[PDB]
Amino acid sequence: LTDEEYRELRYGKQETYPLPAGVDALVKDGEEVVKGQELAPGVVSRMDGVALYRFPRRVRVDYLRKERAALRIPLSAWVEKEAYRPGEVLAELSEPYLFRAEESGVVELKDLAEGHLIYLRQEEEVVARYFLPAGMTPLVVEGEIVEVGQPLAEGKGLLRLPRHMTAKEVEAEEEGDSVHLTLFLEWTEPKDYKVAPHMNVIVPEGAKVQAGEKIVAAIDPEEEVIAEAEGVVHLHEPASILVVKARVYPFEDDVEVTTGDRVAPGDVLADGGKVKSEIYGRVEVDLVRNVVRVVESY
């Protein structure tokens, strides 16, 4: 009777897989993994089970951005839709076009991947918010004083939503030659945070967070990491991953089981008889990922 073989029968199959510093995993914190599957460029799992992160070093936060801007283009070149998708063609310009300033003031240029966003400011007041999709290259620069009628950008061929931008609730009022579109833009803007062991990631993978919300804790304040604004947390670069032979069943509401209990194929776990197990084994009610995992038996 091996000191080890005992733990496998009683508590279950477990294996740790180390990761070379600065390397990122090819799986999420509690993703279902199969025998042979790459858990990271160098590492490869030897069993089916659940991959769990051991002390991650990088926490990425996909911050949500939303701005409302306007665009002026030739009615004939427009590709009328009530919502656009990333990379989506917004219009087809036959000949070069000059999106001209309909307000005056100082410009603020904000790169948005293959696209741009312009703000016309007059003193302490944002007087305008212009959207100019990829293809329409800006003609002005951050800090330039611009006047009404002055061309701000220029499009030559097709106009597309930045690969990562989305536009919905498009309100387009027609006007003779051109068209005036005001769009509600939404795109993700990520930021990365480095976690030194003496730090505790309070939030799990996939968590939605709000401004002010504490993401990472530590005995020192300037060390703490607080969300700039609404977003979605992501864990990256775990020093290692522990695979556990077990299945995982997430639930929307109420758990009908307790950590420690044994289970069999059929046995209900949560959401009324909606969530049933498929295997025999131990139970662990993870309420950090709002899921119930069942460690295989045999």
Image (cartoon, rainbow, N blue to C red):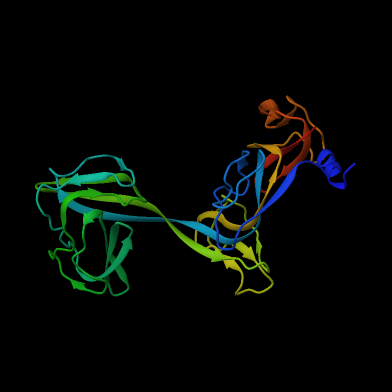
Q: Is residue 234 above or below residue 280?
A: below
Q: Would residue 204 appear left or right of 173 to someone viewing this image? A: right
> Can residue 194 be seen in the rendering of this structure?
yes
Label total for image: 0
Q: Would residue 142 appear left or right of 24 to someone viewing this image? A: left
Find residue 170 and report its image quarter: top left
- Percent position (x, y) of residue 65? 41, 56
Q: Is residue 123 above or below residue 36?
A: below
Q: Is residue 203 above or below residue 270?
A: below
Extreme residue in the right direction? 1
| Between 98 and 197, the one nearer to me in the picture | 197
Find residue 234 and report its image quarter: bottom right
| Between 181 and 191, the one nearer to me in the picture | 191
Find residue 174 and report its image quarter: top left
> Can residue 290 be seen in the rendering of this structure?
no
Q: Would residue 53 appear left or right of 81 to someone viewing this image? A: right
Image quarter (top left, top right, bottom left or bottom right) of the N terminus: top right
- Percent position (x, y) of residue 275? 67, 30
Residue at image position (15%, 44%) is: 77
Image quarter (top left, top right, bottom left or bottom right) of the C terminus: top right
Residue at image position (52%, 59%) is: 60
| Between 24 and 223, the one nearer to me in the picture | 24
- Percent position (x, y) of residue 157? 16, 50
- Percent position (x, y) of residue 36? 60, 40
Residue at image position (61%, 41%) is: 33
